[PDB]
Every structure is written in C-alpha cells, then in structure tokens.
Image (cartoon, coloured by chain):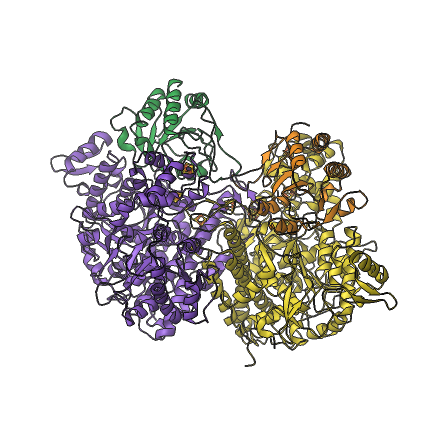
Chain colours: A green, B orange, C purple, D yellow
Amino acid sequence: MVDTTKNTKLFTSYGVKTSKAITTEVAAKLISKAKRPLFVVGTGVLDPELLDRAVKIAKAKNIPIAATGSSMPGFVDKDVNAKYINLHQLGFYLTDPDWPGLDGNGNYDTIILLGHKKYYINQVLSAVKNFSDVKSISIDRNYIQNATMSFGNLSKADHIAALDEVIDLL
Amino acid sequence: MVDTTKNTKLFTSYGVKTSKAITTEVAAKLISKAKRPLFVVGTGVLDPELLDRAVKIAKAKNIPIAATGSSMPGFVDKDVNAKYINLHQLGFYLTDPDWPGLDGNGNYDTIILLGHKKYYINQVLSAVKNFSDVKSISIDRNYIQNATMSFGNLSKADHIAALDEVIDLL
Amino acid sequence: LGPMGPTPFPTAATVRDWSFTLFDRYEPVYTPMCDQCCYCTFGPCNLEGNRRGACGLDMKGQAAREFFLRCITGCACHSAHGRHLLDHIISIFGEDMPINMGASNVIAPNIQLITGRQPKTLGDLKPIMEYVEEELGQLLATVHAGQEGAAIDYDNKAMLAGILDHVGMEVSDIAQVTALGFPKSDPEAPLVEVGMGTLDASKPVIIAIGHNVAGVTYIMDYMEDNNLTDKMEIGGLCCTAFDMTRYKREDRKPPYAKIVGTISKELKVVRSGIPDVIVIDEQCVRADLVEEGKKLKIPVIASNEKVMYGLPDRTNDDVDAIIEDIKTGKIPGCVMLDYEKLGELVPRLAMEMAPLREGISAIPSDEEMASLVAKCVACGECALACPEELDIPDAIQAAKEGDFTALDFLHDLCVGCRRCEQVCNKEIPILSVIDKAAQKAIAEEKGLVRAGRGQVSDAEIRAEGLNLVMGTTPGVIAIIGCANYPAGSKDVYRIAEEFLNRNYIVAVSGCSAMDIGMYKDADGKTLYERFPGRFERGNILNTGSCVSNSHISGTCHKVAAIFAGRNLSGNLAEIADYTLNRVGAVGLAWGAYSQKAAAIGTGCNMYGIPAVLGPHSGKYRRALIAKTYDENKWKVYDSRNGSELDIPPSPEFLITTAETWQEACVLLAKNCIRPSDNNMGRSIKLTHWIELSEKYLGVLPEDWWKFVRHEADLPLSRREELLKKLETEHGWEIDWKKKKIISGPKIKFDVSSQPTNLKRLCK
Amino acid sequence: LGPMGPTPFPTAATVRDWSFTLFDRYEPVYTPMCDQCCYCTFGPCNLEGNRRGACGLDMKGQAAREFFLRCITGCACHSAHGRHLLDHIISIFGEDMPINMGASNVIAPNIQLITGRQPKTLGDLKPIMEYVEEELGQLLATVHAGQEGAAIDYDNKAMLAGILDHVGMEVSDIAQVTALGFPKSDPEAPLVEVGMGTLDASKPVIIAIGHNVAGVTYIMDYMEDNNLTDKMEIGGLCCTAFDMTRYKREDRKPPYAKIVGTISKELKVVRSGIPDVIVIDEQCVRADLVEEGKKLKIPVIASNEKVMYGLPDRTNDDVDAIIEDIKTGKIPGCVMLDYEKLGELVPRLAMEMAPLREGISAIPSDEEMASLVAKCVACGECALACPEELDIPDAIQAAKEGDFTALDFLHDLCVGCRRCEQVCNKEIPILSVIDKAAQKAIAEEKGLVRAGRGQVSDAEIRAEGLNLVMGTTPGVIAIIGCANYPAGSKDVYRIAEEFLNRNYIVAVSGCSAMDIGMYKDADGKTLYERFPGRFERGNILNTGSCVSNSHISGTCHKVAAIFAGRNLSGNLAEIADYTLNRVGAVGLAWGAYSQKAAAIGTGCNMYGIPAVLGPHSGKYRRALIAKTYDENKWKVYDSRNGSELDIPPSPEFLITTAETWQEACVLLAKNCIRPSDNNMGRSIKLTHWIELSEKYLGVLPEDWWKFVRHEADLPLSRREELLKKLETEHGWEIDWKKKKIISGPKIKFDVSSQPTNLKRLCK
Ligand code: SF4
Ligand code: SF4
Ligand code: SF4
Ligand code: SF4
Ligand code: SF4
Ligand code: SF4
Ligand code: SF4
C-alpha cells in the first residue's frame, strides 16, 4: 500500500550488505534533497502508465534524464532534458570523478532508478556502489539489493500508487 | 540480558536463508518441547561457568550429551549421559535416518549447540540443514546463520545471563 | 622457413605489451557478481568497498580472477574437444592426411598467427595441441591462492587464454572438416530443417545432445548401412546438431538428420515425450535428463568420459544384454565408450523402445490443466526464481478465466530451466503448463537453416575488398554465441534482418543461427532462403558450430595478409593493430552464458574485434570500455614518420553489453567506423548509423560530428541539412557556393595516413 | 619391458571402478560453502535444500564440482612448477643426466605406479609431464557448465586429479634433487636456523618469498662468488626457504640461508622493516606486498611470469639503471625474468638500499601504542572479521589499563592477515599493536629444523619392516600441510612430541616442519636435535617442501613392492588396496588452506592413506567418512579362496576434520589399526590408542572390543582387567585358568588371511 517495505525477499544474495527498504516519504525527501540527481531510466518506463509518472517526477525537480537502452523515443515530445547513454557506459563513467557529465558540469552524487531489469541494474550497481561514492534510490517494483535505498517488492498497481504518492509529496 | 536478538551482524553470508534470532523464552520452549533432543557440545564449554550451566541444562530436561572434540573430561564426574563423537562424523550420521544413535534408540529431531567455533559448526550445519530435517537451536554467543534458531551476538556476561534465564524457564 | 614475427608461441610475458596498450584505451570495468571470495579456507573473505582479503587480493583482483577462470575454462573445453577429436581422427584415418579446407593461401590463420607454424598434415596439428595444453596448465596454476595479485595481469592472462581458445577451436574445425567430409568453403551449403515440429512421432526418435560428432558419426553410419534412414528420425540439440548435419555433405545434398533446437529446448523436448532414446556426449547437456527420463521411460546413453552421469559402465558387455536390461527397466542408461558398439546399440535401442513408450508425456490434458491453473494462489515465488523475469503469476491468473494467451506469449521467452517449479509449494509444473498452452505454436515450429560452410575462401574476401573500399559494404556483423536471450529468440533474427536489409555482411554460428532460421516472413521464407549464403554484401553465411568461430576472426586475419601483405607468422600485435585500425567488423553474442562465449569474446578482443553481448553477460564480471570524453585516450602514431595522429572515438568499446535489440542495432552500426576509411566507406557507415539511431532511439546522435573530416563524409541524401546543422550549432566554416567544408574538423582527411598503436612499427 | 598392470596412464573411466569401490565404504560428505552457484550467466542459482539450478545440477553436484576445481587447481600448480623447473634444469645441465635420488630399487614409485614408465634420465621425465598436462586439460574441461551432472563422477575425477598431482610433485622433486645437489636420502641432514629472531638487522637482509628456487639459486651463486655471505643475510619464507636450505647441501655442511617462517609471518616480517629487498617467485605470496613496501621503502622484485604483480617489465634494461630508478623512488619494484641479471640485481639492490632505509618500520612506539590503545571504543568489528576468532576487543581493553599480556597471547594465534584493520573505523593497526606487544617473544623467536632429506631409501624401510611386524613401531604419522592453524603454531609440535615419545614414525614437510622446529624444551633443544632423523621408531625426518610429500606417499608404495613383491607398473588399484588393508600410516594437515593441500589429501586418499585435517578444512566442501554402525559396509574378499571376510572398522575415514589437537591425537592413534596386523602390532596399537583416549578424552573407548580378536591382542599392562570388562559387560567366554579367550569375538584371528577389496585378485 504505502508500506513499500513489507516485502524485501530475494532469490540470491550478493552479500551481507543490502540496500535499505524505504517508504514513499523517505524516498521523496531523498530525491528532493539531493544536490545533483540524475534520473536513470530503462526500457521498462515505456509503459504508458509509468512514462507520464516519470515525466512528472522529472518536471517537478528539473532532474536530467539518462534514457538507457531504447527508452529515448518516449521523451522526444515531453519538455524534459533527456539524453541517451549506454547503461554499462554510464556505470563506468559514474566511477570517474573527472567525467564532465551529460551536460559538462561535472559528476553526480545521487541517481534514481526506474524501469530496469533486476539482473542488469544490479550488475551495474555492483560496480557503482563498490568503486565510487554515488548513492542510488530505486523507485522500481523490485527490491534492488545493490542500490543504497530501494522500494520493496510491489505489484503493478501498488507500484503506481506508491509513485503517485511520491509525486504528490515531491 | 533478556534481549538476544538486537545483534545479528555477520561478516560473510551463506545465502538468502538465515536462522531466526530467538529470545530466551522461545529457546526454553523449543528445548522443552522437543521429542528427542541431543545436546551437541564443543570444547568451548570447558569454561567453568559454561560447564556448570550446560550441566544444569542437561540435568533439567534429561538430554543426552554428545561431547565433540576434547570436551569429554568435563563430564566424567558430573552425573550425566555424555558420549564422545567427532562433529564431522556426527553431522554425517545425523543425515541418515537409519542411524541407531548414541544409545541405539534411533535418530534425533532437534539438536542444541553450545560452545563451538562459528566457522566449524556453520560448516557442519551446512550439510545438516541441507541434507536432512533435523532442527538446530544455537544457545551460543555467536549468531549461527546455518542453524534453524539461534541467539544473537552477545558478550560473555550477556551470554551467561541469557543461559541463566533459559535455565530458570526450563 | 619464412619471416617470423616477434611473438611466436606467446606466453603471459610475451603478450603483456600489447595487452597493456589495449587496456590503456579500453579500460577494464569490473562488475562483481559477489561480495565474497571463497577460494581457500582462510575465507570466505568479504571484499565489499574494494577491501582486501586475508591474502591481500582486493575486490577488483577477485573479479578479474573470476573472469580469467571463466576464460580458461572455456579455452579448456574447446582444446579438450580438439584433442579428443584429433586423436580419434588420426587413429581412424592416419596422421599423414593433407589438410583440405577450400581455396585459400593461408589454411589456418589463427595457428599461423599464434604459433607461426604452417601445418600441412593432420599429424602436424599434434605439437600445436601440446603447446595449447602446456600453456593452459600454467594459466590454471594462476587460479591458486597467492598467485598474481594485480588485476591488470589477470586481464592480460585472460586475453592470452582467449587467443589460445581460438587456436584450439581452429584445430578442432580443421581436423573435423578435413576428415569427416564437411563442406569446404562452400557458398551453396544445403538447407536443413529445424524446429520442434520437424520430428515425427510416428517413427522412433533419437536425440543427440553434445558438441562432438565422433559417436553419432558411427550411429549415422549404422543407420545408413542398415537402411533405416526412412524408418527412423535422428535429431540433434546444440552444436552436435550442426556437426552431424555437416557430416558427409561435400556433395551439396540435403541431409536426413534434423536440428531440434538450442539448450533452452532440451528439457522441453524431454517433456514432450517425442524422443525415444537420448544419447548425450559433452558440453551443454542438462544434468537432470535422467531424472525425467525415469518418469517418461526415455533411456539416456552416455558416450564420453567427461559426462558419464553416474550411470553403470557397460562398455564391455553385450549389446543385447544392455538392450534387455534397459527394456526391462533395470537401469535408465549406461556409459557406452566403445563407439562401434554404441553406433549399433543406440538405433537398436530406439527401435526396441519406441512401441513400449507411445503416448506417454508430461504435458497435461485439458482437465489436468484446469486443475493445475485453479490450484495457484499467486504467491509470487516463481516470478522471483525466474532467470528471465517472467510474469508467471499474472499469466496464471489470466489463464484462470480461460485466457491462455499469456502463457503462449511466455513460452517463447522461457528457456526451459524448471527453476520455478522448485519454489512452488502447490507443486505446479509451470513449464509443462506453458508448453501445453503453446502446443499450437509448437506444432508449427519449423524453419530452414543453411549448413555450416566452413571457412571463408580467399576469392570471396578479395571480391569483397573492393565493395568495402568503394563504400558499398558498410561493414561486417558476426552473430554468434549461446541462447540465453532476455526477450526470446526473435531479437537476434530482427537484428540480422535489419542489418541484411542494409547490405551488411552477416556471418552467423552456433545456436544463434538455429534461432535465426526459425522465423519466416509473409511469403513463408526464412532469411537463409531470402538472402544468399556466400561472403558478400547483403548475404548471410553460416560457419557451423561455435568451433567454427575461429573462421570468423580468422577471416579478419586474412584481410591483413591479403591486402596489406602483412606477415602472419607470430605477429599477433601487428595483425591485431591492423584489424583494430582498419577493419570494420563487430561481433554480437545476444545470449552468451557459457564460458566458451567468454573465451571467444576475449579472443576476439585480443584480435581487435569489438563485441556486444546480451544484458545477462553483465554477470561475466568484466567489460572493456573507453573514455570518449578523454581526448588524450584517442592518440596513435603515424607509420610514415612516427608523428602523433588523432583518431575518432571508434570503436568506443572492446566488449560491452546492451539492454534491448534496438540499442544493440545502434551500437553495432556505430562501432563499424574505423579511422582508416576513405570518404565512401565513412559516408555509408555514417548514413546507416544515423538512420538506425533516428529509427530506434528517435534522435540524431550527439557525437556524429566527431566522425566528419570531409564534406564527402556525410550521407548523400542529407548532406546540405547536415552542413547547416554543423554551421549553425558548432561554428564550422562551410563554402556554401561549392558545398565544401572550409574549416572546423579537428581531424583532417588523409587517406595515405597509416595509424598504428605500436611505435616500433614506425620509421 | 616388465609386467604391466591393468591401468597404465589412467583416465576418468580407467580409475572409476577403484574410486567407486572406495566410495562404497567411505561415502562422501558434502559441506557446501554457499547456497548459490555463480558460474554461468543463467545464475546465480539458489540450490538450498538440495535444489537444482537452471542446468539441472543440484547442491551436492555443485559442492563436488567446487572440491574438484580446488583439486585440479592444486594439481596444476605443482605440475606447472614441475614443468618450469624441469625445463630450466634440462636447459642448464642437459637432458641426459641420470636421475640421482639415493639408494632404492624403485626410483620414482609414483611415476612407475601411475604411468608404468621407469625413467633413467632427465629427458625421460618430459613425456610424463606431457601426459600430466594433457589429462589435466581434460579435467579442467569438466568445470564448464553442462558437463558431468552426477556428484560421484566429480569425486572420481577429483581422485584422478589427486594422483596426477602426486605424479607432478614427484617429477618436480626428482628433477630438482638430481640437478641442484640436494641431499640424497641423507638421515643426517644439516640443521638450519629458523625464526624471526635469526635475521640480523646490521647487515642488508634479502627476503625470498614463493616456491620456485631457479632464481634464488642464481642469487646465492652470485653471493658466494662475490664473497658476500658474511656481509649479507639471506632468508626465505614458505617452501622456497627449504629449497635454498637444501641447495648444494649433500656435503652435510651447514648453510648460510635462513628460514624466516610460514605465510602467516610474511606481512609481519614486512611490518618489521628488517627486509631491505623482497624477491617473489610464485605460489603462496600475499598480494598486498608493494602496498606496504612503498610505505616502508622496501623494493619488490618479481621473477616469474605467473606473478608479475602489475610491475614494470625491466627484463631488457641495464641493472644499474634499474638500481638508480628504485633508489630514487620512481618505481617500487620490477619484473626481472632474466635469471642471470636478477641474481646480480637483487644483492646489489640490497647493498645499495640498506643504508637509505635503516630504522623505518610500522611498529609503533610506546606513546603511539598508548594513544592507539586509548583510541578504541570496543565496537566488536575486528573480532567479527578475524578468521581465527580472536578476542581483540577484550585484549585491547586489557591493554588500556597496561596489561599487554593479552595481545602477547594473541600474537601466536594471529595469522597476520590484517583483515581486522579494514573494519576498524578508528583506523587502528591492530596487527602492528599485537606485534609491538609481542616484541620480546619475536626477539627470542629462534629454533632449529633439519633440512630436507629427500626420499626414504630401501634399506631404512627394510630395517623398519621387522619393527612394524614385531609390534615395536605402532605406525607412521605424517605431519604436512599449510599453516592456517586454529590455535597457533604449537599444536603440530604437541602432536609430534606426543607421537615421538610413543615410538611412532613421524615424517614432516612444508610449513608444518618450520612450525614444529620453532619450540624447545627446558634444555633448550628442538625435536630435531632431540630425536634422530632416520626412518625408524622414535625418529622425526623432514622430506622438504610440499613437492617432497610425494616421497611420503611414495614410501608407502615401496612397502607394497619390496615386501610383498607386488608389481608397481600401472597397478594403482592393487597397490592402493594393499596399502589400505595392511599399512598403518595416517597423514595430518592441521592448517591446510590452499588447493595444493586439498590435492595432496585427495591423492593420498586414492592411494589408501587416511588423513586428518584441521577444522578450517571443513571449508573444503568434502570429506570421506564411513558408516561404522553399518555392519555390511565392512566386508572384503579373501584372496586365498574368494570367500567373504570381515574386517574391523579401521580406518573409519579417509578425510575428516578434527577440532582440537587432543582429538587429533586420539584419531591418529586409532586410525593406524589395520585388519592385517599380527598380535603384537594390534596389541601395541590398541595400547597406545587406549592410553591416549584415557589421557585426553578421560574415558576408555566405547568400541575397543571391536578390535579384540585374540587374548594376545590386549595391552600387556592392562590385560586381566580388560578381559574382565569383556566378560562382564559383553558376555564373552574367557578361560580364566589359562588367560585365554574361549569365545565371543566376531572376527577370528588368522594371520595367513589376505583381505582384499578387489574381486579379480581372488583365486
Ligand atoms: S583466496 Fe584470498 S580472498 Fe579468497 S578466501 Fe583465500 S584469503 Fe580470502
Ligand atoms: S510459485 Fe506456484 S503458487 Fe506461487 S505464484 Fe507461482 S505458480 Fe502460483
Ligand atoms: S522454467 Fe522458464 S518460467 Fe520457469 S523459472 Fe525457468 S525460465 Fe522462468
Ligand atoms: S563467489 Fe559464489 S561460492 Fe563464493 S560466496 Fe559468492 S556465490 Fe558463494
Ligand atoms: S552452472 Fe548451473 S547452477 Fe551454476 S549458475 Fe549456471 S545454470 Fe545455475
Ligand atoms: S574495530 Fe577498532 S574500534 Fe572496533 S573494537 Fe576493534 S579495535 Fe576497537
Ligand atoms: S591480522 Fe590477525 S588479528 Fe587481525 S583479523 Fe587477521 S588473524 Fe585476526
């Protein structure tokens, strides 16, 4: 419901260190308090019921969007600053503090993850969280262990309700 | 004292599934409700305090003792039924439902662990809990992940107090 | 002997300079699969946060060591395959048989490049296997605790293992093609039926799973000699299907053996009950085949020392006794290491077993499906345990109303792993449920795949050179690897069709060829019938099993030898530099899972060939990515004078992973651009890359202007608009009257320039 | 050629019968390290509860595969060592040097037993290495995804890898002993000084870490030629130290090289600042050596391709230039693969570096120690991260008051891995604190250890045969393995002293010999000078490094040959059965951590030699334990007539882990009993076993009566009361007027009976 922490089950574990299961209030606060956030979206955002949610989230705080994979065509019409980048390339670049970024103004401190696959974003975060200091907030419906903070295991309707609650609290 | 669940930290994890951190009341109930329990005791019981605590626990509920390692000399004069067995052998024998046991009356269903090393008892329980159906209760200082139920991470005085409080509820 | 290069029979030290030169630009990126190391009893050690274990090895070193172990495991499985096959071939045919493979001045480009040896007889490959074995042992000795500490020297050893793996694959293919009468550089290889619907249940069915065709060759010999071809059906899973199909196909005639599918089909076909006997040999064989054949009364016969499956060893027993024992249910199979007796036992066992196990399968009926669907309570464990992240609870809930379309959709995406069934407390055979729901699609699952053609001949390469230099062929796309696809077996087909429509050169191999051949257009034609099968623009050719991947990379080597006159003998660094700087070829492993794929990718990287892998390959723990924003990374030397030269950032990776097949298409199109291109080749490459980016990502690329040195480097149909875009957004000065670029490009055009990464190659 | 056995040059299939016969009695017990498999990209797969992964392999199969990978890794590190050493030896001394080992009819028992060959020259060892490599490659091919599925053929392949490991060790040891002038079966090998307190800081100190001795021989040749022996100290860590101390020591003259310690000493020595240059070769070398040497200005020179350490390769540069660069701090070390230039660079580097770095160490001063101790908060992370489970917070809290005895106690138990320091938020160098607290013990840390004697000669075995038969030698105890001890390096010393006082035969090797030689009695004498170094009762002999462990096993083989006239050539099953049924010999690896130890233990098991491992070895994921309560498990054949014979349950295991050194002593005493013992041998073995059980466990064993078949099978001192215990508690009928057992034993006594585990050896 609002819980988003009632289910943090996993099939396999990376280790003893896991991301913290957070609520919608904490997620909204962390997103709206970050100094320089980046909205890293995947192909899963192409759902006609998540793409507008993501667009509203990006518009609320003017967060630049990195549309990894083939999710770029969903951001051409919307008046947002979305750029294409390979997710593996982005994960490699994030660990370098000398990377100018998607706009040339430097690196980022926190990233927001939505619409990815549980085995690809986890692999990228396995490098990001181990060889850098960039924090990650996962607002997906799967419990991402390799993030810094992440939502629980939610259904589609529950995930969309939680995203709406985060939007209203932004 | 009463709290034996506030610390379940680990260095390395075997996997997703982990033992439940129980309290003294639950541990006493589980020990007193077992149909055929076995007190598997390592050489760490040779500490005098742990020695008399274990002797009292075995006397209270008439539990046969398997003195693994070199802990047998601590039970020669005490009026208990303690027998020597290798822990790696005992763990091999427990997975066989056709093993007559330490007295020839059959196999056991619940084992109690006190006074081991967290890297040896964990290795034995790795086989026991994966290739059998024997339940394990760890009343030791360390949080044993491969058990079924275990105490938390406690100090020496805290462990002594917890063992006492168990003995009073036995 | 002739000219020998600086690096014959390389070791870890002998290739360190080239490896470090490559890693300077394409830095390794480590994506660890775990936070702990478990090699010795000092551990398991936690290494989170790049911490070091009890031996001092840190997280990066552990990830590099794990990838190196994967690479050496793959190299050891093509080398062992090669040694076994070559020993059997020499024992049967003699070791003085000339190596015949087609029309090519260089017969074994990989062997000549690595060892500097020109083998002319089957007995001349024996020493090369000894070297490939011996060095291999040393590499395995580095997996110990207390061995190499730095991760960079683990990456170097991984590249050495990759090139050794390519050498082993080359030896394997050379021996088998020379001996067993495979097609030899044949651009008209016969078409082969593929799919689940090809096999006929009215006849006895033999299913061969493995990689080597030593014993199934005897099986086919017995079937042909006794005239049982029309009375039985023989099918193959995995690469042994390709190898058995190519067998005795020098006559360009259609084979009678059929190809069932990839590894993902194995359990599925076992659940179908169609097989009447299963014979297993080696790599890529499920380990629970007997656990199901016991229920379905399907005998499982092992034929290798590598895979014995814990079965009784009846090698010295009578065939009739074994047949009686299997018929009466005493044992579910046996190890039959004697090829002569196996080749008779298997068809006889199928003939004597078919009538006794008709109509038995694990597929549920209608009422059983209704009960099984109504049993579920939507607890979500199966979705959690699904490797491909499939919405199984939603599919079952939709099927509760009688809407079995969701499971039919899920059937293509599933890979037959049965991992869900082990976490279902209701004990629902989910895989069987999906198979029954997709029975209608399974029935019409047919297709055509071209047989393995062997290695590319010299004449085809020479003919394609002109098309490459006159901007007629944009580049070379190799599609290899396994079948661990993230979104079903159609993405590879879509990529191949997209690149074939644009007149690329598509070379396929392995399970990817099988899954490409399974789809047709409106006219009911596969890609192999829609496009020709020779080395040409707009043509798709099949090399065969993955041991033929050594041809693909090998072909690139010949490009260096034929056109630049470069010496191949022991000249890995020079040929690799040439290929990296001049040849526009890229490989794609969309479903790579096994260590063989990792070894092949690493060997391709060491030869200068970039590779794109599927998202699951992010679990390999290593990629090779370049820093495009670092302008000092992209600098080379000029061979004419030793001066410093600038090159465009292409290729931007040596090995990377994409997420969707559209992103894969864009990346493959982009990374075919090379610094040593004339105007026409660069123009056609830019045209295709920009069009694909516009089609699939919806935007014009943000760095296209980097690959623009000349006004003739722009697409023909969109030249003036791109010139306006250059002028109004970047300040470039353009001669609008002459449609010529006056100034603005960082890198000028000089076709006579010779970029190189080795300073010892300059004046 | 002479008579050849049924199994020459074995493969996986060739030794399956013997391995399955062994596993019928001594069943494998799997103790998995995880619940997950992380091999291919289909995973990581969860296998908890013996569930199967996406490939069908279950938890037991995964544990067996992991142990098999450990075994093949160890076999590959002795084989690579052997090949490199043999190639260097052949290049230097020529390939036609006769093998010089000592005085024995069988020179290479392992090679002759496995391959069947009878080498006579250093060039005749070349084929054996080719075989050992070739089969090895095949074995590595089984680690791939999709190979063997059952968990029993993995165990069989593990035993094959073990015997191959023993063959490789034998080859390496024979080559080095023949070439480099090692002692040849000398029962009076020179005594060498050991300990951290032996090296003198006044002179420049060189420290050699690794296993290979090819470069160290050049270094010491240069030191002797230029007369720097008395002006410079040379020391070795790990087995390379043993190799130096055996070099040119057949003259029985004391050497100048000194053994510093085992692997657990390495970092500590680096933290001491005594070394002025560290030269590393390959196996067992910490990966964080440069990371500390850069702080303490200690240069690091690598000399092998296996371990380059990510260092610049200055093999072709001048020695003076490298010395200048290292002196000026440009680089912290270099790879110097040219042995001739390395042997000059290392001593010259030490000479030019000692004055500039004297007085720099990581050991804190008194005020720094006070501050560091007062900084701690007792958060408990260091105790959690300690592999040996050491009470570090309690020690630090006791040190806060001024009681530095707790850290002094902890120093012996600590293995110097610094893993604690990486989880301390206060950044306290705990290892340095413990070292400073134990400075006095470190200063007074000296001892004597006998040099490697080589292999046991035939004459000593023949002399000891009568002692074994007449019940004067209870058995053979081998003490080998690594130094990952659970309770410090004194347990091996205690076990060795306990078994030497009881007139056993103790053979030591590896780091265990070093740690045994580090302790003295009141008279200030070590065990090596307290007991002789021959092969007889009450003697402790040292074979040398781990590559000499083969000699130990080889000795057992000769017992089957020179006494029963058995043929050794290609007769693994027969010799192993003889050893298992007749020879009382047990091995002990109290601190085994590395894959070499696992391979050695598996090879010993396949030869019929049981071994007891330390508790940490429970992380190896496999043991071999028998079901004592199952009376049908202990049944063999009678070689005289093929009848069924009963044997007492001994040995009751092939591999098992003990927990404390007292339990280890009891187990070692018990498992030296064999079914073929005569009355006197059985009597002495029972006497020692019962006495040790009473001493350490405090009770009389509960199954002793299982080994009593004759009245003369009881201890002499306690015969009548044991007879009374048999009569009263069990109902045995005893002739009290003649002190004879009338009836009651299950197994009768028949010294002429010939137990066997092979049906084909009967009648
Ligand atoms: S190899 Fe190193 S990191 Fe791995 S378990 Fe052993 S000590 Fe720890
Ligand atoms: S695991 Fe079984 S019960 Fe649970 S949701 Fe999946 S199919 Fe339904
Ligand atoms: S069998 Fe298919 S549906 Fe089930 S978990 Fe495996 S991939 Fe997913
Ligand atoms: S690397 Fe593999 S075996 Fe080791 S802890 Fe991780 S999952 Fe377990
Ligand atoms: S090898 Fe088998 S168990 Fe291991 S990850 Fe791959 S599919 Fe899973
Ligand atoms: S980790 Fe550091 S602060 Fe914590 S108890 Fe250990 S020494 Fe003290
Ligand atoms: S350095 Fe010593 S005290 Fe510290 S964790 Fe390692 S063994 Fe324990």
* C718 sits left or right of D113 in the view: left
Q: Position of residue D640 (x, y in %)?
A: 65, 76
At 53% across and 37% down in the image, what residue appears? A16
**Quarter of image, res C400:** top left
Figure quadrant, ligand 2: top left
Q: Position of residue B24 (x, y in %)?
A: 66, 30
* C477 sits left or right of B126 in the view: left
Q: Position of residue D64 (x, y in %)?
A: 53, 54
- The answer to which of C190 and D60 lies nearer the viewer is D60
**Quarter of image, res D739:** bottom right
- The answer to which of D339 and C551 lies nearer the viewer is C551
Quarter of the picture holding the C terminus of chain C: bottom left
Q: Position of residue D393 (x, y in %)?
A: 68, 35
- D627 shown above or below C56: below
* C632 sits left or right of D105 in the view: left
Quarter of the picture holding the N terminus of chain C: bottom left
- The answer to which of C276 and D656 lies nearer the viewer is C276
